[PDB]
Image (cartoon, coloured by chain):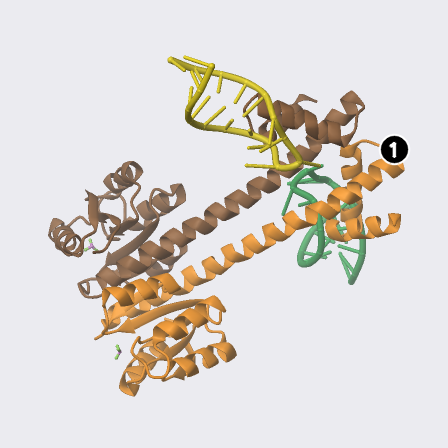
Chain colours: A brown, B orange, C yellow, D green
Amino acid sequence: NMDGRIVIVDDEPITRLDIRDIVIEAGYEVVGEAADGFEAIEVCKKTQPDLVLMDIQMPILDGLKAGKKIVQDQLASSIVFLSAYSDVQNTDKAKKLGALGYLVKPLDEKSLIPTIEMSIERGKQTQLLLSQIDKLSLKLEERKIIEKAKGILVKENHISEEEAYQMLRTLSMNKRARMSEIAELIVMDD
Amino acid sequence: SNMDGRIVIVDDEPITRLDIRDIVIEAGYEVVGEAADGFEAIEVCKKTQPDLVLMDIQMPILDGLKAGKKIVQDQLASSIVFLSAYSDVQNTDKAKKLGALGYLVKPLDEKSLIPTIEMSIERGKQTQLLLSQIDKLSLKLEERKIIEKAKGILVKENHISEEEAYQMLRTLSMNKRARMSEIAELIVMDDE
RNA sequence: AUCGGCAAAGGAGCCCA
RNA sequence: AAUCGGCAAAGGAGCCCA
Ligand code: BEF
Ligand code: BEF
């Protein structure tokens, strides 16, 4: 049966429990619940769920603004709204902040589980791309700092690039630290 | 009022294609084509390059899942949303794996369609931005090896520091307003 | 005297019970 | 001497067009 970790957010517990039944029957893990945007933020912060289901109209903080915080900080992998509100203002706001689905009340208990599976998977793949972008842009920070470190080290010692790389390689290995970090220190040095 | 987006509709029951067509046009979208089987679905996407594809699973010739895989992996459309009576667990696994952005179930809840369209269009665009940023970084990381040769040539020929040689190459490439890789190619062939 | 980890792999160093 | 746009940098503040 289905696999995924889910957080449920609505101010009306009646709807919150309808969802809770459907989702657990399908076999997901319901890890937390919230009745307002602040409980929702703190629950996600602790939880790190795969999906957050939430209503726009809540007390304290509408799901739009709480969702904005959730996605900005990356407290959850994917987020899907459901509300009886579907005016274009709320639709644009939800799509801009980065929702992966939006369902209109009263919810289609038939569509829900499929849209859950889609939103979880596309959430994961989006997190993979962000990690690949992070990894590449880091490696491209590293080579710049490394090349600066080669240059400054050659200027101070008056030696060749092979010896400069050998110095960085021996230091990083001896000191159990990335050549990139050693280079950042040496470049800050001058 | 006045939604923007370009859509293609794909189902074997023409009554449902017309019900959908009427809804999306009333919202303000542009329908740019329709199909009634997987083979026309791929061909229409090749021509139109739409923002969103709406398709049933059970279609003749090529099930919507097979056309959906092709459309996604060749990027013939920026986002894709299924709409079927089939909610079968195997069908949801296939649809999410190939790369759907939504999976509504027949008979459709018309209220829900337009929001899921807007979300799926935006998520499709954003996913293509991220893929473009990956292509740009990985290219610029390959340019580095040519730039590192051009740097080495400057430090020898001028008899200067690495930080001075890069500062020269950068100020040159900005002055001549050309990609450092292009200036690096010119220098490295000039030494040859 | 032995196990484990980080770094390097343009390698073969370092730390811990 | 200034502003609009564009190219390139971003290991940054540089260059072209009205
Ligand atoms: F508060 Be939800 F919009 F029912
Ligand atoms: F008729 Be399709 F399978 F929804």
Position in image of residue B2 (x %, y %): 40, 72
Left or right of A138 in this view: A15: left
Left or right of B45 in this view: A104: left
Say which element carries label 1: helix
Q: Is any part of residue B99 visible from this angle?
A: no
Front residue of this view, candidates B81 and A54: B81
At 32% from the left and 54% from the top, the residue drawn is: A120
Left or right of B118 in this view: A44: left
Quarter of the image for the C terminus of chain A: give it.
top right
At 46% from the left and 58% from the top, the residue drawn is: B127
* Amino acid tagged 1: His
At 41% from the left and 65% from the top, the residue drawn is: B121
Front residue of this view, candidates A182 and B178: A182
Q: Is residue A92 above or below residue A128?
A: below
Position in image of residue A63 (x %, y %): 28, 49
User: In this figure, which residue is indicated by the disc labeled 1?
Assistant: B159
Q: Is residue A160 above or below residue B181?
A: above
Residue lying furthest bottom = B14
Res A138 quadrant in image: top right
Front residue of this view, candidates C12 and A109: C12
Front residue of this view, candidates D13 and A151: A151
Left or right of B106 in this view: A146: right
Quarter of the image for the N terminus of chain A: give it.
bottom left
Res A95 quadrant in image: bottom left
Q: Quadrant of ligand 2?
A: bottom left
Residue lying furthest left = A14
Q: Is mark 1 within 8 Å of ligand 1?
A: no
